[PDB]
Image 1 (tube, rainbow over the protein chains, first blue to last red):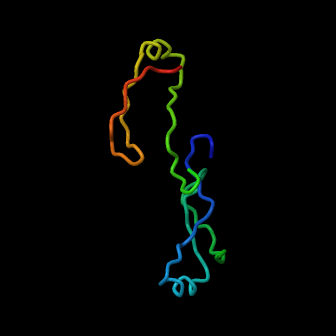
Image 2: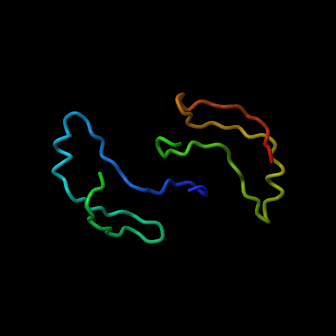
Image 3: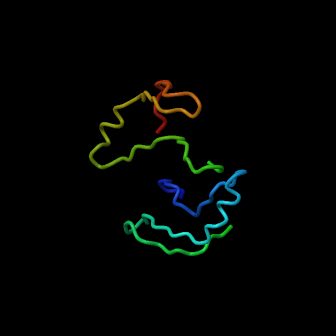
Amino acid sequence: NPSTGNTYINGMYFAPTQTNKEALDYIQKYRVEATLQYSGFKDIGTKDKEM
Amino acid sequence: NPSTGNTYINGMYFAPTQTNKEALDYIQKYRVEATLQYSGFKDIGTKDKEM
C-alpha cells in the first residue's frame, strides 16, 4: 500500500522441498483466522487450497 | 521490495503543525543511526536537512 506501507497480505504459500512433496498433499482444506484492518480478529473461512 | 515485502526506508518527513513552525526551522542538521541492510547498526553521517 503506497500510503504508510504496511504490506497487507494477498495470500500465502508453503514451500515444497524434497521431503514434504508427499506431506503437503494430504491437506485439502485450510482454515484461517486473521486480524483485519477496520475490525479485529475475525474467523475467516475454510475454503480449499489454490495450488 | 519485490521478492519479499520488507519496505526498506528511503527518507523521513516531519509534519508541520501550527504550533511547531518555530522549532523545526531551528534545527539544521540531523544525525542518523539505523539498522542497515547487510551491515549492522552502523552510524551514518550528520548531513543537513533538505526541506
